[PDB]
Image: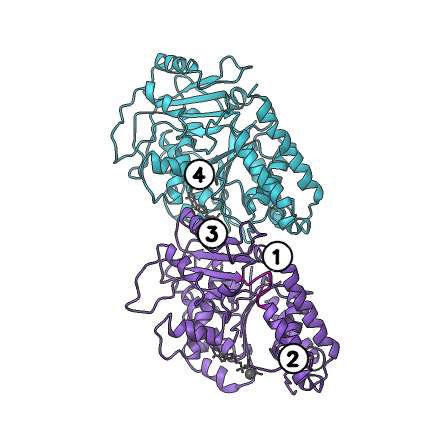
Amino acid sequence: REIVHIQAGQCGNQIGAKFWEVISDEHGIDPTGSYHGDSDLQLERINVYYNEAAGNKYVPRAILVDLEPGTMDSVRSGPFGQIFRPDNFVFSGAGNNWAKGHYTEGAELVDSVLDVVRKESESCLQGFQLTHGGGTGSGMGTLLISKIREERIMNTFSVVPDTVVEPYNATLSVHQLVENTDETYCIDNEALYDICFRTLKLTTPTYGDLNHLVSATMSGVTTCLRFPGQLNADLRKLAVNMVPFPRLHFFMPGFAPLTSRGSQQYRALTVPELTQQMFDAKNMMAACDPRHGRYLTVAAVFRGRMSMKEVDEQMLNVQNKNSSYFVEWIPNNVKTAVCDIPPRGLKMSATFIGNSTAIQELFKRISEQFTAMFRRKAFLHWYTGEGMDEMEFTEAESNMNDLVSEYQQYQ
Amino acid sequence: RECISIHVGQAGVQIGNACWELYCLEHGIQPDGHVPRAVFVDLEPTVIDEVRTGTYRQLFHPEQLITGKEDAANNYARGHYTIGKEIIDLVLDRIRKLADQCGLQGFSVFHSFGGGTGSGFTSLLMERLSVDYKKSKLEFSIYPAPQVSTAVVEPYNSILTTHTTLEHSDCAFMVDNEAIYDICRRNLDIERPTYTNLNRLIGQIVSSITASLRFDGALNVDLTEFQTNLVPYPRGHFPLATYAPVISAEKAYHEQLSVAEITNACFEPANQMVKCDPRHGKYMACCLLYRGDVVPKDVNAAIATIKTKRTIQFVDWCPTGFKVGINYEPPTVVPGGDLAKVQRAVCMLSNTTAIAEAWARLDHKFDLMYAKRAFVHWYVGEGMEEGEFSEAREDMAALEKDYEEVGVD
Ligand SMILES: Nc1nc2c(ncn2[C@@H]2O[C@H](COP(=O)(O)OP(=O)(O)OP(=O)(O)O)[C@@H](O)[C@H]2O)c(=O)[nH]1
Ligand SMILES: Nc1nc2c(ncn2[C@@H]2O[C@H](COP(=O)(O)OP(=O)(O)OP(=O)(O)O)[C@@H](O)[C@H]2O)c(=O)[nH]1
Ligand SMILES: [Mg+2]
Ligand SMILES: [Mg+2]
């Protein structure tokens, strides 16, 4: 099987450097070097992220998309920066109109994209990893998938938060994520800072970091499950256990051992310590706080030798101490997953992929903000004036809003 | 006469290397002797490689060591239909290539019940067998257990494997599910029982089946013998495996336990590699395979005492259902694992009314999932239909009635 990473924007890019910084070592691939792999198993499945050309040069099969040179020119001028084949670096009026990047402006640039998304797929393809309330985002990216899904999965690692029409560009994209995408690990820039400045006494959290933290979660998700386990799952399981209603629904990823370097290295990681972590408010890469709305599904994708008993068990008390918020029409919201090998240097970790709520309590939010401002067409002229439609916004909000109703169908 | 074996999954392979070890060990065939009679499958090279790098390296043919190159998927459908299909041919080929070289009796499969490549795949493997050879499909699994399942879907994968297994899987030795752990907690003491420790066990009980039995003795028991003395009815009936001297090689020392103790310690409700406690299940046939220093009178007495304990109630239509299998060579414990190492053991297996449970509890799971179609779209879109499910459910239904009628009455 295979996948092709996608470093959209600076952030998504900055993180690329960290996602690949890691992953490589978790696959013994030095800058341009080959497989120094301490073992022999970190190679039989690499393909998922590289390509064979020379014989020591397995090049990451990702894409680096960005309209700001300096960025990619910082990622390409630093450490592992010289492993990406230059071909990878893909450096109109990008109006902040969902309809401007989905129907009028983006619709053109699409074919010249699909072109490549095929050059990379035909590099069997599984899906693409994507790291990164606007035009080029909700509209054009929400199109990229609607096309992809007609032609493999689409995991999205978003750094959820800053705009005015926001609910317009949003409601319209969530809509598409219902019949297109189907896997988002909603990470974030200020939910990260927090989680990175108080859960990691880290005082100067550079972007590289945030990115790095995020990339840490998207590794636990995918790649991870493509490892053995007493009880392993894979994108689908994750999908087929987490989406009660077709909207596509968005999640909120959370990593396990998130302790400051020296001191904190408490090792309180028997397991109750990981669920302690993962399930608290802070520590949810999302902005919103779980404590503010039930869950529909949860997927503790652990990856480190543990007792299918102390795992399967804990999950329960957790489900009972908080019966309040965990929705009821799902006897067992939680989807326990269990890999074996842990994050290279750690003893025990567990990625958390939480699905927000059925009284969709986030898409609700978003959807609300829209209407309250759509009603007055607030900053709508910046969309329409960019070749959009008054029916486009209607569409999204309606399509995205419906997701909340369906998701409740299971709560 | 023979019984091929397909060890699937890293685990099924680790357990395989183990069960395969115990074998030669009690047949005097060192590292490099004859030729096995099984195969090894895995989609992760590094593990089968362990059989290619480590011990028992040259006792295999790089031909009976396969890997793969696709996705597992913890979903029946995909494993049975869609993906699993592609491999089957090839799979069969070996159980037709290995079945020829030997009039065989079946394939002892080593992997697990509920799962992606364990439920689905086999479903059609046993499926394609019942038509070809009509033979036996006894799959030796390391699974659950009810309240401690793993996969989120598990039941979907079980209810589907049962229905399509009715004519596919004859008997699934459902050990390691969670009842073998008890044995590791209660009869050996250890909270850290790695999957490797659980296999060493079946790796033992199994050694008592083939290995030693196909090995000369004072009361030999052929494979056919089993099914004959062990299945009262065509349903690929599933007996349960049990071992006697499961004492710890460090804790206690109650080793010297006369045959008049090891036998009885196979009746208790906490030493049978199966969470099917005789909650009522009347035995209907037991094959007491002994090994080591055992006097036939000791047995033809230790068993007599049992036949009259009544609280051990055997089926009605069955006067005597005790196949006494005596071997010579005592067991052979891992040099330094955690198994005691006695000079006699009792690997008694049997059809109790009792899987009446295990099947029940596994069937109900399907109804819960299917009742909502859960992961159904995953199979349909893989060349299956509302038929195969619903019609494989009805299948097992008459396996809940079968295992009920042949007993309790
Ligand atoms: N972790 C991380 N987050 C970043 C980084 N750069 C930006 N962000 C976050 O991503 C969002 C910023 O997106 P922008 O840089 O404004 O825009 P863009 O997505 O690159 O595309 P344009 O709006 O067209 O410029 C904010 O929420 C930032 O906090 C980065 O290097 N790392
Ligand atoms: N008893 C026993 N269980 C094992 C052994 N090795 C692995 N297992 C168990 O079997 C499962 C592991 O399967 P993997 O090793 O990940 O995979 P595989 O089935 O060999 O095939 P791939 O996923 O393609 O590598 C886990 O539930 C382990 O606990 C073993 O030697 N003995
Ligand atoms: Mg930009
Ligand atoms: Mg393997």
- Name the kind of residue labelled 2 in the image: Met
- Name the kind of residue labelled 3 in the image: Asn
Q: Residue at x 36, y 24 (%)?
A: B265
Q: Which residue is mark 4?
A: B176
Residue A388: percent from left, percent from top: 72, 81
What whole-number distance in Å separates the C-alpha atoms at marks 4 and 1?
A: 32 Å
Chain letter, cyan in picture: B
Q: Circle 2 marks a residue in which chain?
A: A
Of badges 4 and 3, nearer the viewer stands: 3
Chain letter, purple in picture: A
Callouts 1 and 2 on one subunit: yes
Q: Which residue is mark 3?
A: A320
Secondary structure type for disc 4: loop
Q: Is residue B341 above or below residue A36?
A: above
Q: Residue at x 66, y 51 (%)?
A: B377
Provide the residue span drawn in magenta: A355-362
Viewer-side residue, B207 vs A342? A342
- List the single residue furthest toward the front: A324
| Residue B91 visible in image | no
Of badges 1 and 3, nearer the viewer stands: 3
